[PDB]
Image (cartoon, rainbow, N blue to C red):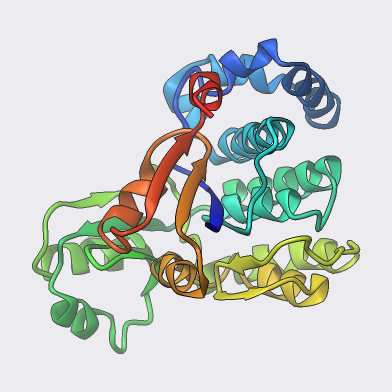
Length: 293
């Protein structure tokens, strides 16, 4: 048996997430750490307005803090990961889970990362479920204003770019539904370049430990544990595509028999269903999940 822990990103947040975790000493502590580092309470913010929670400058550090808490809760129960990965923001949680940086260093990175992306608005992203893979390529080949930002499952991708451009492909690629994401930036595309290049200055000055388990990174989901290759892949992540489909395939084939989504929602196990359906799925995002072992 080999188990992957995978960490969900933006879009998996829901109101009330993490709040039941608060009766554990581990959660209480890290929440207080997050509060001193961030200047606001993650618990309080997770119980706020829905739209407000979805603002990426709230969502990202909220998801990271909760996911790091879940990882440590899992550890305390004795469970340990064989492989880690995370979807966009999730990668940070995965990196913390793998010893690459400590809790606090990670939260500071996430905080800055999410500020950059929140201020780096202008453009737009949309998701496509059940599309003509052929018609997608024609609409994307030679397209300077629209790129592929997530490759999530054979049935699903996310495109990214100018408002005009993304609306176009929407109307002239067979598929529905085709749903604008609740984000207002051209994330995971070259539009993030100038934003991604100041944050990269910050990232390179940060020492990365080697990982205690294999990390499969978004831009290159081949397993590795080298601290410097992982930083390199992470630095590349903000302008680059999330190869999550390939992440799951790599998992299933390098040995992993089980696949645990460590965080709120069912998005990453949902994806795994229609990609590697012979893998065993758990969703660990609530105390109730933890208690069932």
